[PDB]
Length: 375
Ligand SMILES: *[C@H](CNCCCCN1c2ccccc2CCc2ccc(Cl)cc21)CC(=O)OCC
Image (tube, rainbow, N blue to C red):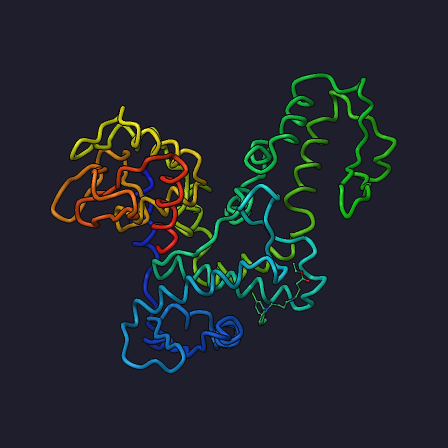
């Protein structure tokens, strides 16, 4: 079979070029109004195919700049706008999570929310088509709905561990004596909201014979049922840029890496293929502070750290042992450099992180995170 790298090349080779399109797609935007200006332009074009042309974006009438770099800035700027929870379209999947899901109440304040989601889909399809990344990460059920993959109980674990444990208990044991009913209770605004799960659900006891249906219905209620129109509108915009049978060569994890440049960063594999300079070592106390700092960093900041030291967002295939610099192969390297009062600097070409010798873990935490907040 094909690994992710071979799948991506296979994918790009089928994404054949349009020639019935204007060769440039021009859009002029003002930074203060980048979302409305982008929405009116992208939702206004004749054919979605116009968005496949080379992007020529101009911000605030700033003339004579690289049309490739400003495109990358636009994708970042429009991502922070589209995925802002204050707009009511997307929301955080949980108070303790940073992953996003579609807000079920998206329509309450946005009567026109369905065209907004189609716009977000077009932008997402544009990022994939033009080889650019979106800034934002969604729950795994989001990527699976894009691929028409069924939402399973395992997907609940990555979002809510305590309810996943409860549903896994139900699956593994006879739940009849608990007298569970085909209803769902949700805690919103200090009040219980009961929702039967099928007609007459309050009178239907969850037994061994119907629990698979029960779990399925709970899964749909949590991730699918209240967002089907928003997701359909998003997919409609996305498939206007990427044919939906082409996207299906990827699984959910590959798709997230392709769209948003994100995934799990095995901190171990990072550790074993790390080299040290000028007195540092694996057992050195600053180094073991560095590694537990990275351990307790969220999955996004682990990525932003690698970008800071490498200069790229992706992890190389087969792990960190095949990591490359600018003049050939080079593993990840931490060097003693400087004095405790300075912030770490990274050298792009040699994948080297010049780390000052910090006198405390909490100091290493802050002085390291402040050097990455500007990436
Ligand atoms: C409900 C408030 N609804 C916000 C309006 C929609 C958001 N916009 C937008 C936002 C700022 C400036 C301009 C626009 C233009 C319209 C548009 C098009 C496309 C997209 Cl993706 C967004 C917008 C929020 C609420 O009540 O709950 C807050 C959590």
